[PDB]
Image (tube, grey):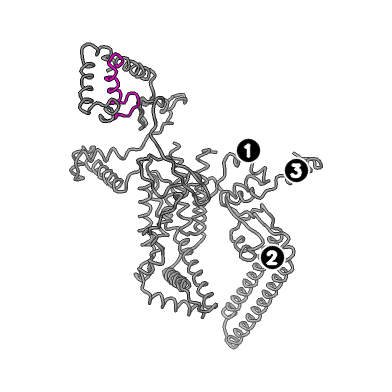
Amino acid sequence: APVTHIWYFKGVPSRLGYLLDLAPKDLEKVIYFAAYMITYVDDERRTRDLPSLEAHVSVERQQIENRRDSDLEARAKKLENDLGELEAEGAKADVRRKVREGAEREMKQLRDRAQREIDRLDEVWSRFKNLKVQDLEGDELLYRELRDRFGTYFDGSMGAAALQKRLESFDLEEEAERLREIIRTGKGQKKT
Amino acid sequence: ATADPVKDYLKQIGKVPLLNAEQEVELAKRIEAGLFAEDKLANSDKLAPKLKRELEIIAEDGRRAKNHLLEANLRLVVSLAKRYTGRGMLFLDLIQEGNLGLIRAVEKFDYTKGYKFSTYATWWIRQAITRAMADQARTIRIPVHMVEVINKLARVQRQMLQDLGREPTPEELAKELDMTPEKVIEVQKYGREPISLHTPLGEDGDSEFGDLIEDSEAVVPADAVSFTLLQEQLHSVLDTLSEREAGVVSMRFGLTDGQPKTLDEIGKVYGVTRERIRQIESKTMSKLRHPSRSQVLRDYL
Amino acid sequence: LRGTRLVVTSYETDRGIDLAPRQAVEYACEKGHRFEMPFSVEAEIPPEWECKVCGIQALLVDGDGPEEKKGKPARTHWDMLMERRTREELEEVLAERLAVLRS
Amino acid sequence: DLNDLYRRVINRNNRLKRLLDLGAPEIIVNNEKRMLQEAVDALFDNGR
């Protein structure tokens, strides 16, 4: 497997960091197998196909809400069945109310889980919207989720192989021109 | 990314929880069925697309089961490998060798024996770890059997020293180990660890152990000049001899070319017989081995 | 201290010597790398060698090298499954797995 | 002391080569790759 040269990684200033514009902490995280790096994204294809993905996610959310209301109706039916089963029973309030409290807590945690999963679906959607090259990505589970959902339209990697792939397809002239323009126009610590 | 990788690996392996016996049996059954489906796919029967899809799905499920078993059991390898720490190999190398052993064990496990999976895995893990430590622990490698003999001798010596209260003599170990004392000393000698050339011996911290080792096989100019003078002086002594004598001596000993030719080769040039070459050489040796020309050459010997 | 690398030397030179005859044999690689090798005239020419460019197996210019099978690719999980288990057991566990899956 | 570092590099490389073609989960493979990079780094500059 490819490996990096310690001289051009560690020595201050981090030459790889300066060339690729990566903070040394991010670079150390990437090369030593602690976070992914996106090395390729198809911007035009995703922009063109955005309506289909939007339709898919809207359909998924609508189905989620349908399942939510179905669960609510099922819970209501179960509560009515419990009430009918224990209506004529004469006992203390807590004895007959423990099961109802348990059912209410079950419904509360069910809707909490539904809220959490729709929120995480929105999180994945937002993460996919603003994905760009050289974007570090920890939280392995999130990466696997995003890969299985939309594995096409991009590529990611780990270790020195990702840095090799980036260095291979790197346009020095364009970045140099951008830096020169910023130096001519910009001022402040950005210029330095 | 942290300065310590052992902690990172340890905290990473613990995310996957453990497994129970029924889960292990079910995973093994999944692996078996998936592989048999893979073989059936390897067979060239068309069957139906839906059946092919189902067979592929169960094969993937079996692969997932094998993986899951491996992640679940990595903790056993980590636990086993920690008591072999030291002795050259580092901790993570031992862990990885144990992981290879565990993979080998998982490749060859069965549930019909009704034993918990930990036993077979433990045997194979220990076997792999000890073999690896036998093969990757010394700069000058030693075969497995010799390492075993060294370990046995060291253990016996330690036990004898502890129980008896004195250092055992070579004869005591020889009679205890059932081998000759020469073998005992040879086994003791084979096991030593090479010193390092960079160990500092200067109190101020400037010198090293390797700066005082003489290059024994170094061309000494005095010896080279002496040999050159010998080579130049040898030819002159042959010069005073007759033409044929010097020629045959040079060809026989290959002074001019370095290839000692046979008697027939020498006689071919002059056309004399083999026996003649035999005699002519002898007279030259008698002449040189005389108290009349030896003095010029006595010193160089 | 005294020390010696396990190296031998001889008081001998290159000047005034006649070199023995040699023959140059050509070898070719799969990717197109060609090279020459000097061998003594009183020598046998092996059929196979390693390349001087990419470190891969190479043969002579004229090919006369057949393949003899090597006996140690056997180790896989499948053959062990054959060795450990019969076919009927695999068939019945397979049938059970299909039944539970389609259930 | 350079023989030891070269031996570490070669051992890690050979073990990684065996693991890759044997077929293994990503965890141990990634750990082996990290060890190989650390070994090469220790070979070139040690303690940096």
Looking at the image, which residue is at 63% across and 54% down? A37
**Left or right, residue B290 beside residue C63:** left
Question: What label does residue B173 carry, if any?
Answer: none
Quadrant hosting residue A112: bottom right
Which-is-in-front pick, marks 3 and 2? 3
Point out the tag, 3 or 1, that comes first from the N-terminus.
1
Kind of residue at badge 2: Asp
Point out the tag, 2 or 1, that comes first from the N-terminus.
1
**Left or right, residue C69 beside residue A121:** left
Question: What label does residue A122 carry, if any?
Answer: 2
Q: CA distance from mark 2 to mark 1?
A: 40 Å
Number of marks in picture: 3
* Quarter occupied by the C terminus of chain A: top right
* Chain under disc 3: A
Looking at the image, which residue is at 62% across and 46% down? A25
Seen as rendered, the residue at the extreme bottom is: A88
Seen as rendered, the residue at the extreme right is: A185
Question: What label does residue A179 carry, if any?
Answer: 3
**Left or right, residue B185 beside residue C8:** left
Where does the magenta region start and end?
A: B238-261
Q: Which residue is mark 1?
A: A12
